[PDB]
Length: 40
Length: 49
Image 1 (cartoon, each protein chain N blue to C red):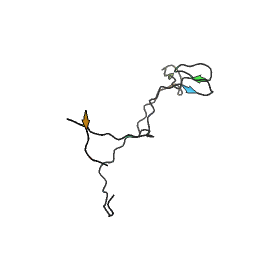
Image 2 (image 1 turned 30 degrees about the vertical axis):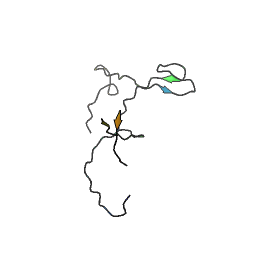
Image 3 (image 1 turned 45 degrees about the horizontal axis):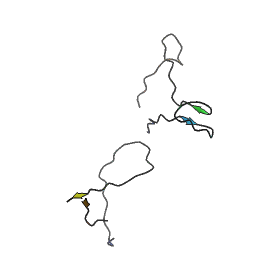
């Protein structure tokens, strides 16, 4: 992680109003099986 | 500002309800008694917030 300061402006205030207690990120794969590039 | 749409049976004891009512298991959903021949308590009211 680089060391520095970066402002984070608000983008979208979505009024969902539901219960959330877990999450899971998504990933996109490339087909040549499957090969994925370097990411973090 | 949260809507609950879960149909799971409420469990009070240690016996699993297995999706149906029974011992220490009751249906959370109850129906209204809206009738025109009754009093204010059974009179439906359209509430907008």
